[PDB]
Image (cartoon, rainbow, N blue to C red):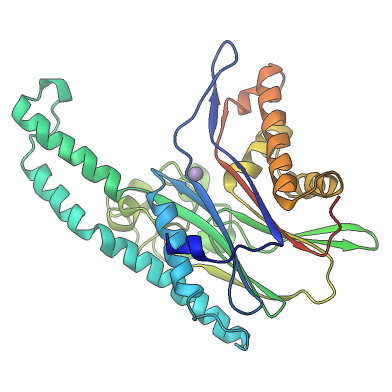
Length: 355
Ligand SMILES: [Mn+2]
């Protein structure tokens, strides 16, 4: 938590809300601990770092990634006078170090887990286990919490008024430019899913059947084809149907880095958002319009709110209302909105007027 001493960026805002499942009858929701996270830091120079992270299976990986990525980038590694090629290399190394050091951090616990499993009669219902093996089982559950979890991440670095985006997974970055002819919205990164052809290709080159992968859509509760952490899929993919044939890790942690974006004389804002936010909007309004809608909602709030945090939080709140109303209306799409995931929205302003 040395990051709590880091200068926060005054040109950005974050809005968020936790996952929720609606109760069948009546009003009342249930939530599991939130697993999203973010960061908005300004370094020495006119150097800025922003990120939105989406975890699953706990939030230990989400926090490990946020903390370590900060350590690998805001402690000197990023320099104003660096060439684009340098910045690409620095981001690439930061993610590689974050992934390798995370896996090294759980190694011992993985070994202890294996040893405890060897002492435990396999396949026996918890209640039928005598007291002796009960204690071991509990220790196994404690180790499981300590080593499990995964995370997707989209990061954006603003260096000498040039913008870079590093992305692993399905979070999104949008650059919204106010042109003479409306608000121009462009998604800077690309979603790493079984619908991303280049990823179906990468998975094809490893020996997996792209057709079956594409059909199924999800690889272990997650549709993201790139993730950080997640030992289940990084080590035991050999034993996972769709992945069985893989010659090397199907799910990787390498980021896709997107070309420098000049921002000189650009007026608008940058949006980083988690999968939970846009997926919820699409569950309620239908396939493919989340980007335009979210950017339009943010546009509207820019004129009414008095801080970027309020701008971001208002949009997150509107999406939550749209979503619960749809489920409550019992209407046509109610079947798609019984619950929603964590939502995070970060907005970094580039001269757009507020209030
Ligand atoms: Mn999540």
